Image 1 (cartoon, rainbow, N blue to C red):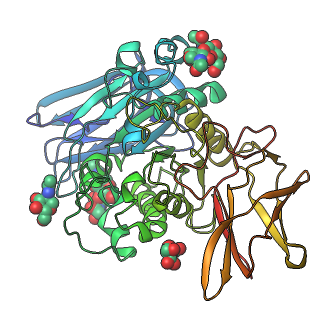
Image 2 (image 1 turned 135 degrees about the horizontal axis):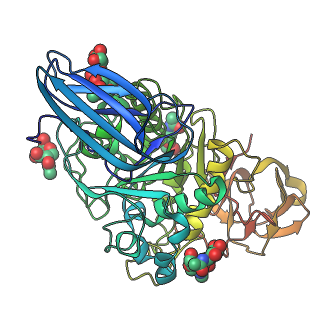
Image 3 (image 1 turned 120 degrees about the vertical axis):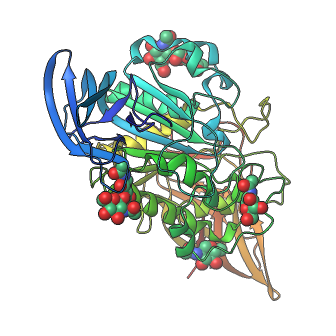
Length: 487
Ligand SMILES: *[C@@H]1O[C@H](CO)[C@@H](O[C@@H]2O[C@H](CO)[C@@H](O)[C@H](O)[C@H]2NC(C)=O)[C@H](O)[C@H]1NC(C)=O
Ligand SMILES: *[C@@H]1O[C@H](CO)[C@@H](O[C@@H]2O[C@H](CO)[C@@H](O)[C@H](O)[C@H]2NC(C)=O)[C@H](O)[C@H]1NC(C)=O
Ligand SMILES: *[C@@H]1O[C@H](CO)[C@@H](O)[C@H](O)[C@H]1NC(C)=O
Ligand SMILES: *[C@@H]1O[C@H](CO)[C@@H](O)[C@H](O)[C@H]1NC(C)=O
């Protein structure tokens, strides 16, 4: 921070810069009015050169490289010329590829040394040396920071030691496994930046713009059993996300929401879509338009934990994570994709059931959505959801017609119906009565009243591991939870 001429903190040896059609932003600090020349080299050969100057009343400089085909290695040099003085900066083993930012709370923070099969996962790096990794230090700030205050893991080739460095240290398992899966598909460099902090609500990760857009109340005394990390508005946006916003990138994956179970829960269907839109706007502008204005944003629908049976804050958050549609992308969440995780539970996790150890399936399901939404591939990435319902009240039956094929295991409490009688509505279990390839028939005979709604898997812990009642027969994806109201 005392060195006058330097790169921004996202720039280092071994990094990945965003590939074509975007141009990669390179920025740093230097002496006011100095000229800065940025050169991309392949050893001694000049690939491209960009020239700029440090603005007269600020001490930063920025260039945008021409778009690059993925691959490498390259070296980036920056030279500051100021009068008769010459200072140079150099980073090597630079690759061009897709840069993904991974963020959220503790289930993004959980590292490869904490997951199932860790020994073998930590050893599987030789084929993935072009999946480069980076982890942001846990820092909060009361104002937006221009540059990261601290980096835990600077850009690196993956090794046993840095993938599994410590419990909730680095490297994020969901992030790593997502990138590894993407590398299998894309076969060009992937950069992974993890920026997460356990026990944090979405308000900490939101700029003031998205909070204002949602009418979020002014902060009071926020800390509780479920909010254990920084909870002041925007303090993690300020320090751990905003400093990256000028860096060109491909997309974001996100795993957060547990700490909103009792913190502006009823606003999460606003604050999460608003965060996505605000990060998009801010990163698009910061990167001089190079990051896509609607860059793909993927997220994990909350998994389960062993809660009180009556607690339905997690089901509410899961619904709000989809802006109350049940699926993404949707009208309020364009170019988003979701991994369902409620069936990826872990009764015996040494980190608590709130921190389940199967991150492999989470990253697999995320990478399906990325392939479809971020890369345009015709790959199934959504689980079966009803597209219409037919109530046969005289027969005591409710037909659910699904838009995909279903594989169904008998489970007479996973569906519930809202039965309104005697001036009250109660949720009653709805047994499964009959099955066809895309139609499930529920029995409603226990409802001696009017049927107002139906819901599925509306519980904090709806099933045992990979034993939810409804899956697609071959995509491996579970039916997502939902609620649907009768006309
Ligand atoms: C444990 O981790 C290892 C390493 O990732 C897995 O073995 C790899 O499995 C993939 C399939 O996902 C193969 O494509 C690779 O060739 C394997 N690599 C190595 C080095 O063996 C193994 O499948 C994992 N097992 C469990 C139960 O998670
Ligand atoms: C990172 O992006 C921000 C925008 O989000 C840049 O700030 C803008 O800079 C332009 C050009 O100097 C000004 O006209 C705008 O008023 C600035 N906007 C804001 C909101 O500050 C910022 O300069 C970028 N960082 C670097 C190093 O260039
Ligand atoms: C959060 O803001 C409150 C109220 O302004 C203040 O007491 C404190 O400085 C902040 N907390 C932390 C941990 O920074
Ligand atoms: C968010 O959910 C709450 C609680 O169900 C509801 O009252 C509100 O209308 C929802 N808002 C949006 C924008 O979906």
